[PDB]
């Protein structure tokens, strides 16, 4: 509703930007501020035009140069910014699954918050890039009910449109209420089938009906009736169906509120949402947490890494 912080620049001159960036890198050292002052003030599409212009104006490769000159978390953010939107998601999913470990939080976040149409583009691109099925990789990297949720989301087969079947909304709400009072454990299949199959309008109506019949929010019941990564995935679906901006505020809060910082999450959220809904994220952050997002980033990061994240945030003093 308020939208993003990062917008398409006016007066955009790709060749001039190419020259600014080369000047920033050429010779010993780097002018990191100059890099920020260009890249954080162009949108992702414009940054692709810079890449093209850099080859033809400078006779070099921009990403290669950035990678050579920069390091650490600042390099990660800048290279992130330079990556086409779909490919960035693809590469984040790959990173989350590569090796014996898994970044489960990353999988949840992307697969719960992207639309089916976005998931299909991601899935296609992952297949083309790696010659691997996204669904098959997810299936390998996760287990049990958590796997069922993530495989379903990755398959991108949720009902679409906004058709409202009042009788089915009622039935679903009742079914979820009963699934929670089954004698020998929650019926987790009912939860995951409703939450993974139904269209958004329908689910928003189920959530309201569930509260009407149970006097409890569906999130409260999820928290008391499920556990583990499976719980976390179901909560992510619900939160994303209600208000994805709020979900991402929560993701940012959790990435910073502890001792230390979940940089991978902070970076991905800030890069991936700066053009979509960062102003809404900021608003919801302030409501939930009574502090500005800006102040959290300022307090938990430093250096050029801080600088660029604060430009992505927008604001604020
Ligand atoms: Ca240099
Ligand atoms: Ca793995
Ligand atoms: Ca911290």
Image (spheres, rainbow, N blue to C red):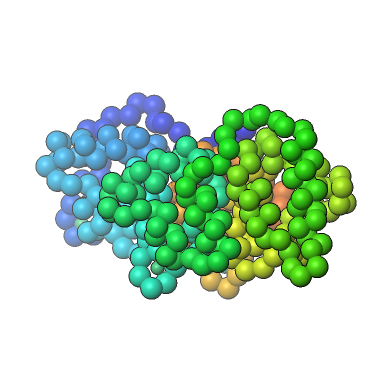
Looking at the image, residue 150 lies above or below residue 18: below
In the image: residue 192, left or right of residue 217: left
Q: Nearer the viewer, residue 99 or 10?
A: 99
Residue 75 is drawn in which quadrant?
bottom left
Can residue 292 be seen at all in this image of the molecule?
no
Name the residue: 64% across, 38% down: 200
Name the residue: 35% across, 43% down: 124
Position in image of residue 308 (x %, y %): 43, 51
Looking at the image, residue 9 lies above or below residue 139: above
Which residue of the protein is positioned furthest toward the top in this rendering? 11
Position in image of residue 17 (x %, y %): 27, 37
Name the residue: 79% across, 63% down: 182
Position in image of residue 173 (x %, y %): 78, 46
Looking at the image, residue 146 lies above or below residue 152: below
Quadrant where the N terminus lies? Answer: top right
Residue 219 is drawn in which quadrant?
bottom right
In the image: residue 11, left or right of residue 200: left
Position in image of residue 234 (x %, y %): 64, 56
Q: Nearer the viewer, residue 271 or 93?
A: 93
Q: Nearer the viewer, residue 262 or 30?
A: 262
Residue 227 is drawn in which quadrant?
bottom right
In the image: residue 18, left or right of residue 80: left
Can residue 7 be seen at all in this image of the molecule?
yes
Ligand 1's image quarter is bottom left
Which residue of the protein is positioned furthest toward the front in this rendering? 183
Name the residue: 31% across, 63% down: 71
């Amino acid at each position: 509703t308020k939208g993003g912080t990062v917008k398409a620049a006016s007066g955009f001159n790709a060749m001039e930007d190419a020259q600014t960036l080369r000047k920033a890198m050429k010779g010993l050292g780097t002018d990191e501020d100059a890099i920020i002052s260009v890249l954080a003030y162009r949108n992702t599409a414009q940054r692709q035009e810079i890449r093209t212009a850099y080859k033809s104006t400078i006779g070099r490769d921009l990403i290669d140069d950035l990678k050579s000159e920069l390091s650490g978390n600042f390099e990660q953010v800048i290279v992130g910014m330079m990556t086409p939107t779909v490919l960035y998601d693809v590469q984040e999913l790959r990173r989350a699954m590569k090796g014996a470990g898994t970044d489960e939080g990353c999988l949840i976040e992307i697969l719960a918050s992207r639309t089916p149409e976005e998931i299909r583009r991601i899935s296609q691109t992952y297949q083309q890039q790696y010659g691997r099925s996204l669904e098959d990789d997810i299936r390998s990297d996760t287990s049990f009910m958590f796997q069922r949720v993530l495989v379903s989301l990755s398959a991108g087969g949720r009902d679409e449109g906004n058709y409202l079947d009042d009788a089915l909304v009622r039935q679903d709400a009742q079914d979820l209420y009963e699934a929670g009072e089954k004698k020998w454990g929650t019926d987790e299949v009912k939860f995951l089938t409703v939450l993974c199959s139904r269209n958004r309008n329908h689910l928003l109506h189920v959530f309201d009906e569930y509260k009407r019949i149970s006097q409890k929010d569906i999130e409260q019941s999820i928290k008391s009736e499920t556990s583990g990564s499976f719980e976390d995935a179901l909560l992510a679906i619900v939160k994303c169906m209600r208000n994805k901006s709020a979900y991402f505020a929560e993701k940012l809060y959790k990435s910073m509120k502890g001792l230390g910082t979940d940089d991978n999450t902070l970076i991905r959220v800030m890069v991936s949402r700066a053009e979509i809904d960062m102003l809404d994220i900021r608003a919801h952050f302030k409501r939930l947490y009574g502090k500005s997002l800006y102040s959290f980033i300022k307090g938990d990061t430093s250096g050029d890494y801080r600088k660029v994240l604060l430009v992505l945030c927008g604001g604020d003093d």
